[PDB]
Image (tube, rainbow, N blue to C red; front, side, top):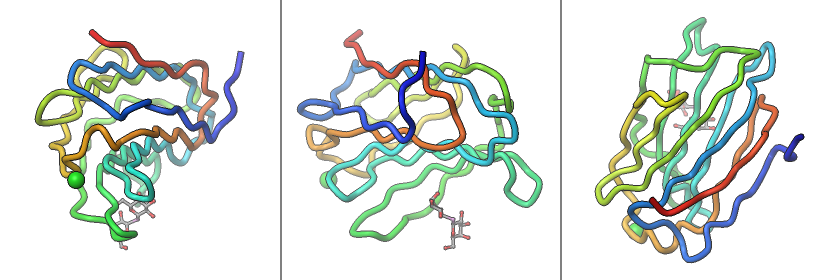
Length: 139
Ligand SMILES: OC[C@H]1O[C@@H]([Se][C@@H]2O[C@H](CO)[C@H](O)[C@H](O)[C@H]2O)[C@H](O)[C@@H](O)[C@H]1O
Ligand SMILES: [Cl-]
């Protein structure tokens, strides 16, 4: 069944438009956080961070970390995750943005702040999940 969390998925030669990343898992009961970290070495090109309790609200925080400094957050109040339930996250790399769908519904787009797509060569998956599968394909 499981993969180990935190999990590091290599993206050989980085990301490219038409690359589809699929993450299957189950949110733990009483989850606090999920994080996907697309990394360019020490930098986080794209941090996708559902928070289950931020001041008693559920919010998705997206950001970029450059030279160990976080940038301007992009916050999404649409929250498709539920504690205890199975999910599917799909991240489709497009020319201008990452497109995220959860459970086959469009959730958000994140404009590319890191422009060297071919150097975004690691996805880190962490937080309060049982991880089932993490894979990529070209569509
Ligand atoms: O932006 C994304 C980052 O956010 C920080 Se928390 C962050 O702290 C800021 C003050 O340093 C502001 O309060 C932001 O609102 C808060 O989300 C998290 O510790 C980090 O893991 C990451 O998710
Ligand atoms: Cl760059």
